[PDB]
Amino acid sequence: GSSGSSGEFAIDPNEPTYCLCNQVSYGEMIGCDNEQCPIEWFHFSCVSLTYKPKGKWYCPKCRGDSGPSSG
Ligand SMILES: [Zn+2]
Ligand SMILES: [Zn+2]
């Protein structure tokens, strides 16, 4: 990558986005065990991850579904 350049937190229309922060893949990323998941791609730092977990990892968007807006 680039040694260092100001102007972070920017989403370019050139490259797509997956992670929740909607940013271009970078650093370490894992594939949500849930295939159906349209993202199946999230950053570590974002998902408070230090290293590839030796266990099924389900994005915070899948594991948290129960609970509809209205009752
Ligand atoms: Zn992210
Ligand atoms: Zn998922």
Image (cartoon, grey):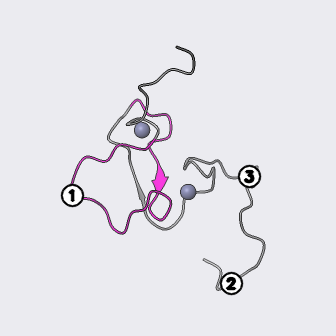
Quadrant of the image for the N terminus?
bottom right
Q: Does the magenta stretch include residue 45?
A: yes
* Residue indicated by mark 3: 14
Foreground disc of the pair 2, 3: 2
Circles 3 and 1: CB distance less than 8 Å? no
| Residue under the image location 45 percent in, 56 percent down | 47
Q: Earlier in the sequence, mark 2 or mark 3?
A: 2
- Residue drawn at point x = 50 percent, y = 59 percent: 46
Please tell me in which quarter of the rendered image ligand 1 is found.
bottom right
Whether residue 22 appears in magenta in the rendering, the answer is no
Q: Distance between the residues labelled 2 and 3?
A: 21 Å
In the rendered image, residue 39, in percent from the top left (x then y), is placed at 50, 40
Task: For marks 2 and 1, give the CA distance.
Answer: 32 Å
Q: Mark 3 vs mark 1: which is more N-terminal?
A: 3
Q: At which x and y percent is residue 45?
A: 48, 65
Q: Do the residues labelled 2 and 3 touch (CB within 8 Å)?
A: no
At numbered mark 3, what does the secondary structure look like: helix, strand or loop? loop
The residue wearing badge 2 is: 4
What are the residue bounds of the magenta stretch?
36-60
Identify residue type, mark 3: Asn
Disc 2 residue type (three-letter): Gly
Around disc 2, counting alpha carbons within 10 Å, would you say few (fewer than 14), some (14 to 19), or many (20 or more)? few
> Measuring 39% from the left and 63% from the top, which residue is drawn there?
49
Q: Is residue 34 above or below residue 71?
A: below
Question: Is 51 located above or below residue 1 in the figure?
Answer: above
Residue 54, numbered circle: 1
User: In the drawing, does residue 40 fall left or right of residue 56?
Assistant: right
Residue plotted at (35% across, 43% down): 58
Amino acid tagged 1: Lys
**Residue 14 appears left or right of 54:** right
- Work out whether mark 2 precedes mark 1 in sequence or the reverse, and give the earlier one: 2
| Along the line of sight, the residue nearer the viewer: 14 or 71 | 71
